[PDB]
Image 1 (cartoon, rainbow over the protein chains, first blue to last red):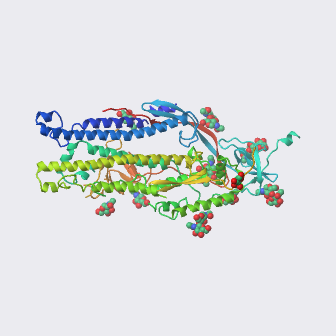
Image 2: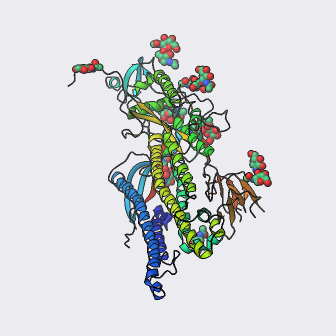
Image 3: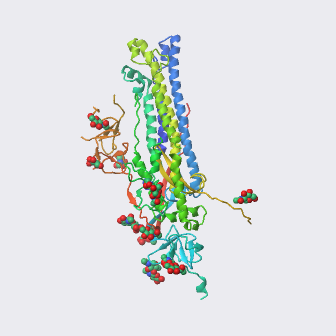
Length: 211
Length: 311
Length: 116
Ligand SMILES: *[C@@H]1O[C@H](CO)[C@@H](O[C@@H]2O[C@H](CO)[C@@H](O)[C@H](O)[C@H]2NC(C)=O)[C@H](O)[C@H]1NC(C)=O
Ligand SMILES: *[C@@H]1O[C@H](CO)[C@@H](O[C@@H]2O[C@H](CO)[C@@H](O)[C@H](O)[C@H]2NC(C)=O)[C@H](O)[C@H]1NC(C)=O
Ligand SMILES: *[C@@H]1O[C@H](CO)[C@@H](O[C@@H]2O[C@H](CO)[C@@H](O)[C@H](O)[C@H]2NC(C)=O)[C@H](O)[C@H]1NC(C)=O
Ligand SMILES: *[C@@H]1O[C@H](CO)[C@@H](O[C@@H]2O[C@H](CO)[C@@H](O)[C@H](O)[C@H]2NC(C)=O)[C@H](O)[C@H]1NC(C)=O
Ligand SMILES: *[C@@H]1O[C@H](CO)[C@@H](O)[C@H](O)[C@H]1NC(C)=O
Ligand SMILES: *[C@@H]1O[C@H](CO)[C@@H](O)[C@H](O)[C@H]1NC(C)=O
Ligand SMILES: *[C@@H]1O[C@H](CO)[C@@H](O)[C@H](O)[C@H]1NC(C)=O
Ligand SMILES: *[C@@H]1O[C@H](CO)[C@@H](O)[C@H](O)[C@H]1NC(C)=O
Ligand SMILES: *[C@@H]1O[C@H](CO)[C@@H](O)[C@H](O)[C@H]1NC(C)=O
Ligand SMILES: *[C@@H]1O[C@H](CO)[C@@H](O)[C@H](O)[C@H]1NC(C)=O
C-alpha cells in the first residue's frame, strides 16, 4: 500500500519521449537554414534566378539537408541499441524475477528475493520486488564445535550460540534455539584439531527412553 | 567550444557560423549527456554501501592476514599496498577536460567500507543490518555453500590461512595486466590529438587561417573561402561527437558488468560458472584502480585425485 | 587566454530565485559576497563550509550545494553515516524478527517508430 504514496520515479520513461521529440523538433528546424546559399527556399531561387546558377544554389541546400538526415538516422541507430539493451535486461528479469526465484544479489531488489509482480507502464515495465529483510539482532557467544565423549560434534545446519549460561543450536536466519542432540549434529574428528572448540553436553534420546 | 574550435577568435566569423542553425547546440547537448552518465557509472559500481565501515584496531582475523588489501595508515592517501601499484602503471584551442565529481580519496573510502563490512559480517550487511560472526566461521559457511563439509576448515584452519596468505602475496609479484585501463586513456588522447591537428587543413581553400583570407582578399570571395573551412571543421566536430557516444556506450556496458559483479561477487556468494574467477567461488575483495576496478577472486580448487570403483 | 563554459547553480525556481555561478577552471581574479576557490574553478554566491551532508546539487570534485537556513551553500560532501561493526573472535549477531519490503525498479522497453 505504501507504493502508491511514493508515486501520487518515471524519469527514465519521460527521457525516452524527450529524446525523440527533440530530434524531431531539430530535424524540422534545420530546414530554415541557408547554408551559405542565396535563399533557403527552392522555389524562390528560380523566381529570381536563371537555371545555370539555380542548380548550384539548390545543390548546396540539398547537400545541407541531406547531411541533416544522415545525422538523424545515425543517432537513431545508436540510441536504438541502448533501448534494445534495456529491453534485453527487462526480458531477463521477467524470466528470472517473475517466473522464478533468483539468488543473484541485487538483481531482483534489495534484500532476500521472495517474489516479484509486473506492472505495465507506457513504453516500459515496472517491477514490484518483494524481499525478506532481517531485523532486531542480538549478540551471542559462539563456537565452531562441541566436545562430548572426547569427540567433536559439528552442526548439520546452524550455529552454536550461548545465552550466557547454556548453549543451543540455532538456524542462521532466524533466532530459534533447540537443544543440542545426536540427531541435530554429526561427528567428525577429535577435539584436538578444532581451534575454539568448547565443552558442553550433547543429549542422546536413547538412554532416557530406556530409563 | 564550438565557436572557438571552428572560427577561433575572429568575430566576422561568428555572424557566418550563426547561418548554419543549431549545430553547436547539438554538440553541447550530446556531450553533456556523456558527462552526466560518466559520474553515474562510478556511483553505481562503488556507491553500494550505506555506512562507512571500519575494521577493529587489532586487525587479526584468526590468522588470515589482509594487510595487503587494507589501507596503510602511514600514508597521506590511505591506499592499500596493492592499490599503490595499480595507480603506478597507468588544454587546446577550445578543448577542456572537466574534473570528476568523486575524488579518488572518496572512492578509496567506498572500497575500504566494502572490505571492512565483508571481513567482519560477510554478506549480511548487504541485505539489512550488519551481523557480526567470527571470520573463521564465515569461511566454513562458504565451503558449505560449494558442497564441502564444514569440518574441512575447522580441522585445517591453520593450513588454509597460511596457504591463502602466500597465494595472495603472489599477486604483487605478477604486477611489479592493466592494458584495458591504458587503452581508455589512449583512445581519448588520440581523439583529442586528431581533433586539434585537423585545424591545419585547407580543405581546398586558398588558406587555412580565417584572418589571412581577409588580409589578402575581398569580402565577396572571402565569405566563400571561410564557408569552406567552416564546413570542414564542423564535419570534424560531428565525427568527434559521434564516436564519443559510440565509445561511451561501451564503457557504460563495462560499468554495468562491474556493478553487477560488485553485487554478486563481493556482497554475496555466486554459483555462476566463471563469473567470479576460475574454480569454486569462495569470496572476492575489491581494489580501486584509476578509472576502473580490480577484483581479487578467491576460489576453491580440488587437487590430487585418486580413482575408485563405485556403484 | 582563459575561458570556459558558464553554468548557473539554481536551487529550483519553485523555491527561490537565488543562483550561484561556477566558472570552470577560472581563477577568481580573472572573472570580470561569497567567493570560494576550488580546484574545479571559481565558485561565486555560495559559502564553503567544513561540514558534510548528502549530495544535493553536484558541483564537481567532491563539492555540492543546497538551500540551507534561505541560502545556498557548498561543502565537501560526506559519503555516509559512519559505523563500526562490533567484531570479536567469539561473538555473533542473529536476527530475531524481520520485515517484508517492497521496492520498485523501472525499465524502458521501446521508442516511437519514426519514418522520414
Ligand atoms: C539461558 O536460557 C536458559 C533456558 O531458558 C535459562 O535457564 C533456566 O533453565 C531452567 C531449566 O534448566 C528453566 O527452568 C528456567 O526457567 C531458566 N531460566 C530462565 C530465566 O529462563 C537461563 O536463565 C538463561 N541464561 C541467561 C543468562 O539469561
Ligand atoms: C573439556 O573437557 C575435557 C574432558 O574433561 C578436558 O580435558 C581434560 O583437560 C585437563 C586439563 O585441563 C586434563 O588434566 C585432563 O586429563 C583432560 N581430560 C581428558 C579426559 O583428556 C578439557 O580440558 C576441557 N576443556 C576446557 C577448556 O576446560
Ligand atoms: C602480514 O603480512 C605482512 C607481509 O606482507 C607482514 O609484514 C612483514 O613482516 C615481516 C616479518 O614476518 C617483516 O620482515 C616485514 O618488514 C613486514 N612488512 C611490513 C611492510 O611491515 C605482517 O607482519 C603480517 N601480519 C601478521 C599479523 O602476520
Ligand atoms: C516482530 O515485529 C512485529 C512488529 O513489526 C511485532 O508485532 C507487533 O507486536 C506488538 C506487541 O509487541 C503489537 O502491539 C503489534 O500490534 C504487532 N504488530 C503487528 C503488525 O502485528 C512482533 O511481536 C515482533 N516479534 C517479536 C518476537 O518481538
Ligand atoms: C553487541 O555488542 C556490541 C559490543 O560488543 C555492541 O556494539 C552492539 O551494539 C551489540 N548489539 C546489540 C544488538 O546490542
Ligand atoms: C580472542 O582474543 C582475546 C584477546 O583479545 C583472547 O583473550 C581470546 O583467547 C581469544 N579467543 C580465542 C578463541 O582465541
Ligand atoms: C586412474 O586410472 C586411470 C586408468 O584407468 C589412469 O589413467 C589415471 O591416471 C588414474 N588416476 C590416478 C590419480 O592415478
Ligand atoms: C512546487 O510547486 C508545485 C505547484 O506549482 C507543487 O505541486 C509542488 O509540490 C511544489 N514543490 C515543493 C517541493 O513544494
Ligand atoms: C589565482 O591567482 C592568485 C594570484 O593572483 C593565486 O594566489 C591563486 O592561487 C590563483 N588561484 C588558482 C585557483 O590558481
Ligand atoms: C576547514 O578546516 C581547515 C583545516 O582542515 C581549515 O584550514 C579551514 O580554515 C576550515 N574552513 C573553514 C571555513 O573554517
